[PDB]
Length: 136
Length: 138
Ligand SMILES: [Co+2]
Ligand SMILES: [Zn+2]
Ligand SMILES: [Zn+2]
Image (tube, rainbow over all chains, first blue to last red; front, side, top):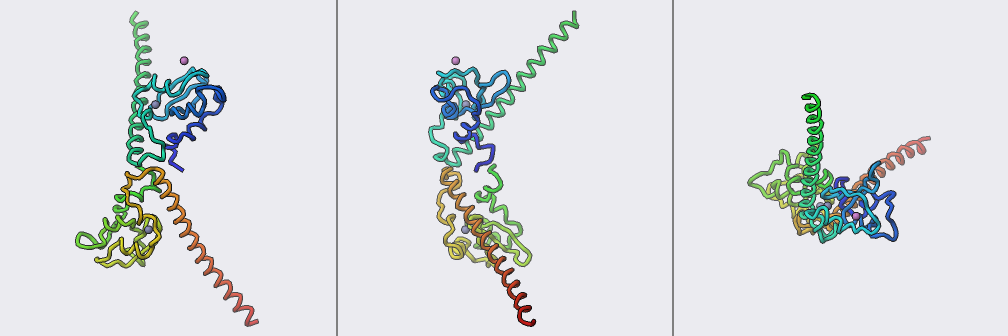
């Protein structure tokens, strides 16, 4: 086994996160392909087909049977290292892996920082809204 | 920042396990040479210089300043896979690692199994004697 934090590096673990995925058997964006492209399944009320790259954390919804997880991945996050890892998990050296887990950790941080930023911006709109109604 | 169970694979972790190791600067079995050979410092009371291979689990106490940890280790446990690993830690592929780790768990179990055996054997000898002391005198 691997510590939980590094399990999503395993393709077969990423697959297993796909429970109740609509596009199965004869589609292009099959669970295996979603997985091979680094995607993990994480549904919500609004978006039920929401998927996220375990590495860069980009989120994509609105999938269609003809979609190719890999091109979609490129198209929305071309600066994602996982998109370069040519070797398979076992073929990597602890040094390469550790370098990767660290890029990922920065990635995480970047996403968390980008969210906190969106929220701040949202709060700003509200405060601006309030001051305006009040300044009237 | 690997998980605890895997930290002993790091020479530095093992080196740091040496607290109050008698042999320093001028000796052969220094902490580094000890760590370099897989040893970790787990001292008891009866034995303050107890050292154990993090991989096969063989223990060794009573070290003199001129002992070569690797030599000793090659003698008291020649089967230890770790004595074969030539690559540095970061130079190992995950497959090579995962396999080294699997075999280490086998080595642990094997140790636990023999303790359990010896303790069970000791218990049996006492039960056997106690029953004899009775079914003899009456
Ligand atoms: Co589309
Ligand atoms: Zn990505
Ligand atoms: Zn050993």
